[PDB]
Image (tube, helix red, strand yellow):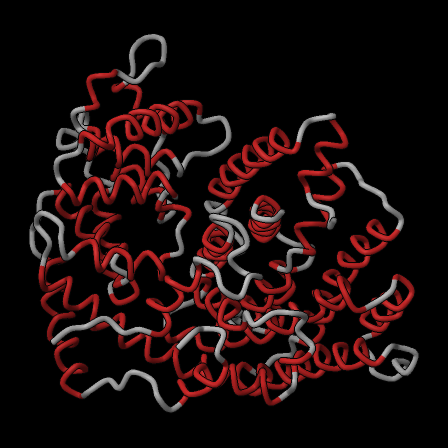
Length: 522
């Protein structure tokens, strides 16, 4: 059974994993034994390692209060003797505390450097310590040159030392980390990878391992049902036939699930896959089905947000416009019923920025114009669609109708998250205009050098986003990680090319193990 088989996808609404009452009971028992692990007196570094594997296994949504207490208690120890001079301990402490909003200066790594700012080369025996530093180096901000050097230093030693690793489980971790750092992987996808990797690690706790498979399957059964209900809506509305040469519906659900996987985020996840799925069809409409003048009518019809003066639109654009208009209005009604507030005005502004961004790209393409990279980038962060999808997610979790006002003008959080997703997509694509061509045209650089440069811009916009995640004045979790998870989805879908638009790519392996196949227990 393939993931592009919609008959099979529609069958998940009734043929999903069945969670037995014995599994409900065993998960409750294991949850309590793990809670005891968090409360029991542990050496500080052993407590950090319990949080790390609980987060990596995807179980962190069951112990958010425990992880916060543990992390906050380590943030005020006062005694630094258990980590100072220790690479692994210093690296994990810096990463775990910065990942929850607790700032830790880059200066804590000055002690592993020489007087010229070179990390001492005696640290290559401790590969686990280099791995932890590598992972912590990606939490850096703009101007933290010690973290940059650590990243460069660890990538080199880890690459060179990889064939000399005797512990098989550490080699696996090092290969996985060099491919993508843990800060750039989507937590739900890494959870399934780590469940299979943890079972073979040194002092793997069998209780945490059984709770991870149990909870994973339990949460995976909730996705399968929504996936089957999504496939039935897609095929029933005939959106199936508006999509141009594509059978990539599950990819859209994988992205939505990457942003919000916990079962309690049903509204944000279903709301984001419905708007995103429909957005791939308006994308197809500005890119393949309409002419410059036809899309201008579409664009102005979106600014008026009306289905009145739409007779002047071609057949395929008439259906696409109505599909986008209806589904968004239907989501507005669903949100008025579930949260008691009107999102329609917030959705209209997001759909007009989206279509205006598609209109600039279409006009540029029509007149053979290639703008400066900065002008293309400001439009490109909108045209990628994350401002509309991330706003859709904020609509599902806002505190009241007046809180929807924080999304206009676009906040730095969504701005930088969307810019990264635009450039990451550009880098995973090979006559449509991208950032690569815009930089080539502005500097006379070659396609290979232009691509290496944009890879560097991505690296610097991650540093801005990292520091921008500390300004918790307007947004807070879980919306901050909804934003980070959207960029992590981009890294996963474009790691080796187009893994989102190609119906059969390397992306089906992880989509099948995360959304379709349950883990075996016994």
